[PDB]
Image (cartoon, coloured by chain):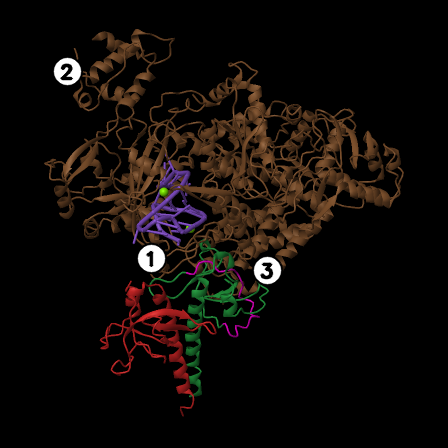
Chain colours: A brown, B green, C red, D purple
RNA sequence: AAUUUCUACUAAGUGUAGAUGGAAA
């Protein structure tokens, strides 16, 4: 038994097969004459209308119920907030009071004032008819009587609104975290400046116009927050601040405008108020998108005004509190250090040096775990003041002034773009083409939106997330401008989704056929209520739907052997036995079935469930009650073949229900005379759609799809319970999205060219027409049948532990290792239990194998063509969604090449871990697509299955492996999942695999002191004359940050040549370069150790160039970026034999024993880490295996990589 | 008068454009995809004789599939790759890269692009 | 007052006939030898709208090999077989099989002829 | 450049090779 054969039948897993339904015979004319489409097309076209109406009613209900709320904890929250908490374990009760507050706002929501007749079927049936005064708006909601089940998802999303899950889509979180915050903030901002606005200029007016009762003070006074929860409440609050309209063109001036004009003092800088938040593009026509663009970005719209306000606000960066403006720590510091200082990692390094001088001792070297903790403490830091960022720089270089310069530069960029786009903003513009094909119009939209958006993404860093004293005089204006500028995201995401949108459309609606419960399940007894069956003739499976008024039209049909007989699929499965049997037997039917009191009293206690140790007789007493009642209840005794097990097998109650559910599946075949059903079709009494997809058609010979195999096995005889037909099918209709004036067709008998350059046959002469998107130019019914694979699973156990136990006890476990690369989209190498490489290759050429011949579709030259295509397209918006839809239709043909090795080797898989890695920007498969790969390789291993295998054998479609848990979320990809070990990827590609060397120095030039200390930190610099090499004997103890290594005594050499990047490229030879460098300065390099000789030259031109060659010696990763044919990794250190590792000595081998490219090295060293983890599993005891760590830290990894090769 | 001839010679120009596109579409339909010339595309007829190459609203890309319409048989082309859905009715092969268009390629060169 | 207008019509109709012969040279090049249509070859540009079939000069034979000229790109045609050494520059397909021309076969029917 | 749908195709001629969980917001 291989390691895999144990993993099947583990857990339940439901999928949704789809198909095309072809109306057969005279059913199309009947659907057209009875008009069963324009009705169901009118419904799912106005359903958005009833969504609008239900939103209106929910808002009216919320505003009618929040005029009775009372936040009693408010009088204490208001004082608890302004305590200067200084938590000291006292803010936890603050959190608790806040939670109880948001809950006591949802008590009336969840409990009273309705909320029952709100989300059930009642609201569209009876409640909403009252809540209306129009006939139009009543006709819609009256037409949905009975079709409430077409909402349940909407009602689902509308329960997120009444709960307090601490999410943006809730009411309580809105009126607690984003109102009370701003409420108290503005209240204190007023308390500061209360006596500024004198009476006779603001008060006498804001009294008479707004309310003239509890006029202006009460809204700031006390607990009147119990009034600013409605919409009229927040409207009157912004009327206090922003002002009124007085129903004419007066526009009296508001509090914020009064603080604005109170700049008469010209030294005001006063903190302005903030409003309250309140709860509740195009993509239709080219003219609409152009109008929305002009209305949302022209020089009058609010976005350009906000750009002007930000230009002004950052032009005055001097007159603000330089200790109150906070850049946000995170990704933005990486670039802020490049703009402000001049290097990529200045801020992080200054902060690391400071943290060294605080927390670290004066140890002669750092410790790996200490450096990790320092990185962690940095990551925890929230924000940085401009003052600190001033401290990290030297003198004669401000930080506020440099930021002012940078922001002004970006704003001048935006202005220049707006100047190069004036042609589009004229009101009298017109188009010569459609926007999707027009590019000198989309290139301008993109050049403008990219400018505005890369300004908005560089400004956002000035927020810093919740702080100490800040500069309110800055943040008032900043937030007021930025919250407006933020709408460019909506615009840029709703114009790109219109210039990218394909020409056709998959917009469908649902067919009900005048029946709410249509097709909701396949049961024999309920046919006359669901009206849907699945006939089968020969090898073709027909749907069958009766009508509205002839529900009894498929019963009186006998076999009668007329040489035509539709089969018919029946014998309903069993619905939820764990609740069904208690429901189907305790539904008050004890009147005239049995006589006993012993069973009835243990029912009264209900002592047959858990909540006790265990019992042998009480549990099986109820088990036998159910058993000897079903074996006499005729509705189930005749239907199912209830062959239960013996009495000693039961050990719990769940076993009984699992057995009852496993036994209640008997999809059976009845017969029916073909002429009678055909006449039923012709009489207009039965609509017979044929299920279809290109693997059912007679002219197809190759391998069928996967889902076709599942749908055929749904009705096999060797499918006992593994793939069963979970009820709930659906039938949708898709209108034609292409005008028949727009089909394009490769005409008949005209030789066509073949797009695949690796294909031998370079033409094709088909004797018919090959339309383009023929499927989108015709009305197409589609059918959605859900199935439930492995419904009743037997082998229940945890997988993360069983894989570990199976690896420990195994002697030779293979390990596949998958890593991206620069010249290879995905390199694979599979290494056995010792460390040998048993197979290694690249996934660039996917070799498709059919009918005994194999043709290799490349996927790198193809992606290279699409990149060269994107390079010269002038709009890059549909030409960069094509690459994103190729790279995700490539990692669906890699998934097969991985689920082939996982079965050929019984291996585990070793994937890179994406939460803790920075791949260097030239690797082809970027991270956003990799995460889509690791999520597509989990969803496949959930039910791994081989199409070309006997459907019963282990591995085939009925008993497929389940070697991974379901996919939870992208952040739960760490340290284990089934057979998929997630291993970090540090020191993985730049590490020579013959020895285990790695380059831990720092060989960039800084000065002459550092350089002389460097050349003095070695042990030997000697020209061996017999080998013509410059032996550098180094000991890693002298240098810094080299606490990771293990051997710590290396003999570097100068063997081989290197490829300096210079983007130029220059092939240098190391020994010759050193000879030339030493001759250029007169250094007699034949005196063994020339260490002291090397520390004599005193210019800056020597140590600036010696460090260069010393760096080129420790490279091991030479690339040219021009040829995939010459890239290679070479090591400067001899191995146990004496020869260097030169990856060009293995490219010319059929199956080498070491990595060939420099990308096979990446995946080889990603698989070795998992071999080390397997090593760890062979230590602990089977009770501790669930606790062994897998995250192999750099010290452990270098040790394992330097001890294995001897 | 003399302003009707100049409303009829602009109908000889179009019967020349159609002939040129039909001559091309049978000389592009044969080259294997990695050799198709760089073209200047447009949805309004492009005279390959003069073409005023200096106009800034015509780019130069490759030409992908050359299909043929359904109702009539007007030979639509496909700039770049198909999945861009950039279907253009009239092309003319040039010898320039993306935007620095050098000169209009003559049909003899497009023919000798296959060898 | 008709100095050059005739020289405009004589160019428009010739360009139309050339487009027709270029649309037909393919539909001929993609057929089996035994399914070619019956041509009325004349080596002078012929029209497909009328063709004046009453003239006793237009013949009726199956077309031979359709060869693309090498000096210019003209689609020349052969008639019968290469043993007749007949070479023409303009043809039109008709369903007048032998010598009596009932009708001129339209393009969609010389395509469908396969 | 055909498809339940996506990607790559033409794959021996109305198709080939992998993948595919839909509905909903
Ligand atoms: Mg297939
Ligand atoms: Mg395609």
Which portion, as a residue range, is magenta? B48-66
The chain carrying label 1 is: A
Q: Is residue D12 left or right of residue A530?
A: right
Residue A1051 appears at what percent x and percent y?
A: 76, 30
Q: Is residue B57 placed above or below A466 in the rendered structure?
A: below
> Could you tell me how far apart the alpha carbons at marks 2 and 1 are, in whole angstroms?
72 Å
Q: Is residue B78 left or right of residue A778?
A: right
Q: Is residue A1122 visible?
A: yes
> Could you tell me how far apart the alpha carbons at marks 3 and 1 are, in whole angstroms?
49 Å
> Could you tell me how far apart the alpha carbons at marks 3 and 2 are, in whole angstroms?
87 Å
Q: Earlier in the sequence, mark 3 or mark 2?
A: 3
Q: Main secondary structure of the magenta part?
A: loop
The image quarter containing residue A195 is: top right
Residue B65 appears at what percent x and percent y?
A: 44, 58
Both on one chain, marks 3 and 1?
yes
Classed neighbour count for the residue bearing mark 1: other residues with Cα under 10 Å, few (<14), some (14–19), many (≥20): few
Q: Is mark 3 within 8 Å of ligand 2?
A: no
> Foreground: B82 or A874?
B82
Say which residue label 3 marks: A418
Q: Is residue A962 placed above or below C106 in the rendered structure?
A: above
Say which residue label 2 marks: A592
């Amino acid at each position: 038994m291989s390691k895999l054969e144990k993993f099947t039948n583990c857990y339940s897993l439901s999928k949704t097969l789809r198909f095309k339904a072809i109306p057969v015979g005279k059913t199309q004319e009947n659907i057209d004459n009875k008009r069963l489409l324009v009705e169901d097309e009118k419904r799912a076209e106005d359903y958005k209308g009833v969504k609008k109406l239900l939103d209106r009613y929910y808002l009216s209900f919320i505003n009618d119920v929040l005029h009775s709320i009372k936040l009693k904890n408010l009088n204490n929250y208001i004082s608890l907030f302004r305590k200067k908490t200084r938590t000291e374990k006292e803010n936890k009760e603050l959190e608790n009071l806040e939670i109880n507050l948001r809950k006591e706002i949802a008590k009336a929501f969840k409990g009273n004032e309705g909320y029952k007749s709100l989300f059930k079927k009642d609201i569209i049936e009876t409640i909403l008819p009252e809540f209306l005064d129009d006939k139009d708006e009543i006709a819609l909601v009256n037409s949905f009587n009975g079709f409430t089940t077409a909402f349940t998802g909407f009602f689902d999303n509308r329960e997120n609104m009444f709960s307090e899950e601490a999410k943006s889509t809730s009411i309580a979180f809105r009126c607690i975290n984003e109102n009370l915050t701003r409420y108290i903030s503005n209240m204190d901002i007023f308390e500061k400046v209360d006596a500024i606005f004198d009476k006779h200029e603001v008060q006498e007016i804001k009294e008479k116009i707004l309310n003239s009762d509890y006029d202006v003070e009460d809204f700031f006074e006390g607990e009147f927050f119990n009034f600013v929860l409605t919409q009229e409440g927040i409207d009157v609050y912004n009327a206090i601040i922003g002002g009124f309209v007085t129903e004419s063109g007066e526009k009296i001036k508001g509090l914020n405008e009064y603080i604005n004009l109170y700049n008469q003092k010209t030294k005001q800088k006063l903190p302005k108020f903030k409003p309250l938040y309140k709860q509740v593009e195009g993509y239709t026509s080219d003219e609409e998108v152009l109008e929305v663009f002009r209305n949302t970005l022209n020089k009058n719209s609010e976005i350009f005004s906000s750009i002007k306000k930000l230009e002004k606000l950052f032009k005055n960066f001097d007159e603000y509190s330089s200790a109150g403006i906070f850049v946000k720590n995170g990704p933005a510091i990486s670039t802020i250090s490049k703009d402000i200082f001049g290097e990529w990692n200045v801020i992080r390094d200054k902060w690391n040096a400071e943290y060294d001088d605080i927390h670290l001792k004066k140890k002669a070297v750092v410790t790996e775990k200490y450096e990790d903790d320092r990185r962690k403490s940095f990551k925890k830091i929230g924000s940085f003041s401009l003052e600190q960022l001033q401290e990290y720089a030297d003198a004669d270089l401000s930080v506020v002034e440099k930021l002012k310069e940078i922001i002004i530069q970006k704003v001048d960029e935006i202005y220049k773009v707006y100047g190069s786009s004036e042609k589009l903003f004229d009101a009298d513009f017109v188009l010569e083409k459609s926007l999707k094909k027009n590019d000198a119009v989309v290139a301008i939209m993109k050049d403008l939106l990219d400018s505005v958006k890369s300004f908005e993404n560089y400004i956002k860093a000035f927020f810093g997330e919740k702080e100490t004293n800040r500069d309110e005089s800055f943040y008032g204006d900043f937030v007021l401008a930025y919250d407006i500028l933020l709408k460019v995201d909506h615009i840029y995401d709703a114009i790109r989704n219109y210039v990218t949108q394909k020409p056709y459309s998959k917009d469908k609606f649902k067919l009900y056929f005048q029946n709410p419960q249509f097709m909701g399940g396949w049961d024999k007894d309920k046919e006359t209520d669901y009206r849907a069956t699945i006939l089968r003739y020969g090898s073709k499976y027909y749907l069958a739907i009766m009508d509205k008024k002839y529900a009894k039209c498929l019963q009186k049909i006998d076999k009668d052997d007329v040489n035509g007989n539709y089969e018919k699929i029946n014998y309903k499965l069993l619905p939820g036995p764990n609740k069904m049997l208690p429901k189907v037997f305790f539904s008050k039917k004890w009147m005239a079935y049995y006589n006993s009191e012993d069973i009835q009293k243990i029912y009264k206690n209900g002592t047959f469930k858990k909540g006790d140790m265990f019992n042998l007789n009480d549990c099986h007493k109820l088990i036998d009650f159910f058993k000897d009642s079903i074996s006499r209840y005729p509705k189930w005794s005749n239907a199912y073949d209830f062959n239960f097990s013996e009495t000693e097998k039961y050990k719990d109650i769940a076993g009984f229900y699992r057995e009852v559910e496993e036994q209640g599946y008997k999809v059976s075949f009845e017969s029916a005379s073909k002429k009678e059903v055909d006449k039923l079709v012709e009489e207009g009494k039965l609509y017979m759609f044929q299920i279809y997809n290109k693997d059912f058609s007679d002219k197809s010979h190759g391998t069928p799809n996967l889902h076709t195999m599942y749908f055929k096995l749904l009705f096999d005889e060797n499918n006992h319970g593994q793939i069963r037909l979970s009820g709930g099918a659906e039938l949708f209709m898709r209108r034609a999205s292409l005008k028949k004036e727009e089909l394009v067709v490769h005409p008949a008998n005209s030789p066509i060219a073949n797009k695949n350059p690796d294909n031998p046959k370079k033409t094709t002469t088909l004797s018919y027409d090959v339309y383009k998107d023929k499927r989108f130019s015709e009305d197409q019914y589609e059918l959605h049948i859900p199935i439930a694979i492995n419904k009743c699973p037997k082998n229940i156990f945890k997988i993360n532990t069983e894989v570990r136990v199976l690896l420990k006890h195994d002697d030779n476990p293979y390990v596949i290792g998958i890593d991206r690369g620069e010249r290879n989209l995905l390199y694979i190498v599979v290494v056995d239990g010792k460390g040998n490489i048993v197979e290694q290759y690249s996934l660039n050429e996917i070799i498709n194998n059919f009918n005994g011949i194999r043709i290799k579709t490349d996927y790198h030259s193809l992606l290279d063509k699409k990149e060269k295509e994107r390079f010269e397209a002038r709009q890059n918006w549909t030409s960069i969604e094509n690459i994103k839809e190729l790279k995700a239709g490539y990692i669906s043909q890699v998934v097969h090449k991985i689920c082939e090795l996982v079965e050929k080797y019984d291996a585990v898989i070793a994937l890179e871990d994406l939460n803790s890695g920075f791949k260097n920007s030239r690797v082809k498969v970027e991270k956003q697509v990799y995460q889509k790969f690791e999520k597509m390789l989990i969803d496949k291993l959930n039910y791994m299955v081989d199409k070309k295998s006997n459907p019963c054998a282990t591995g085939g479609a009925l008993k497929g492996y389940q070697i991974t848990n379901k996919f939870e979320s992208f952040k739960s990809m760490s340290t284990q999942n089934g057979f998929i070990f997630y291993i970090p990827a540090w020191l993985t590609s730049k590490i020579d695999p013959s020895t285990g060397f790695v380059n831990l120095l720092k060989t960039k030039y800084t000065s002459i002191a550092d350089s002389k200390k460097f050349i003095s930190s070695f042990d030997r610099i000697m020209y061996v004359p017999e080998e013509d090499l410059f032996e550098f004997a180094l000991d890693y103890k002298n240098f810094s940050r080299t606490d990771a290594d293990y051997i710590k005594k290396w003999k570097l050499y100068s063997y081989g040549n290197r490829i300096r990047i210079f983007f130029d490229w220059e092939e240098v030879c190391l020994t010759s370069a050193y000879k030339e460098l030493f001759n250029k300065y007169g250094i007699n390099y034949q005196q063994g150790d020339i260490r002291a000789l090397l520390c004599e030259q005193s210019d800056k031109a020597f140590y600036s160039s010696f460090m260069a060659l010393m760096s080129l010696m420790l490279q091991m990763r030479n690339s040219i970026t021009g040829r995939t044919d010459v890239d290679f990794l070479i090591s400067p250190v001899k191995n146990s034999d004496g020869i260097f590792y030169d990856s060009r000595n293995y490219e010319a081998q059929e199956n080498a024993i070491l990595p060939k490219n420099a990308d096979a090295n990446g995946a080889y060293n990603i698989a070795r880490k998992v071999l080390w983890a397997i090593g760890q599993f062979k230590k602990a005891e089977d009770e501790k295996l669930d606790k062994v760590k897998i995250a192999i830290s750099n010290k452990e990894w270098l040790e394992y990589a330097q001890t294995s090769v001897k | 008068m003399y302003l009707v001839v100049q409303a009829l010679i602009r109908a000889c120009i179009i019967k020349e454009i159609d002939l040129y596109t039909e001559q091309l579409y049978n000389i592009i339909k044969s080259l294997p995809y990695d050799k198709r010339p760089n073209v200047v595309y447009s949805d309004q007829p492009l005279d390959p004789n003069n073409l005023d190459l200096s106009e800034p609203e015509l780019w130069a890309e490759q030409v992908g599939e050359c299909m043929r319409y359904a109702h009539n048989d007007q030979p639509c082309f496909y700039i770049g790759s198909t999945k861009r859905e950039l279907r253009v009715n009239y092309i003319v092969p040039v010898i320039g890269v993306r935007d620095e268009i050098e000169r209009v390629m003559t049909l003899e060169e497009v023919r000798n692009l296959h060898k």
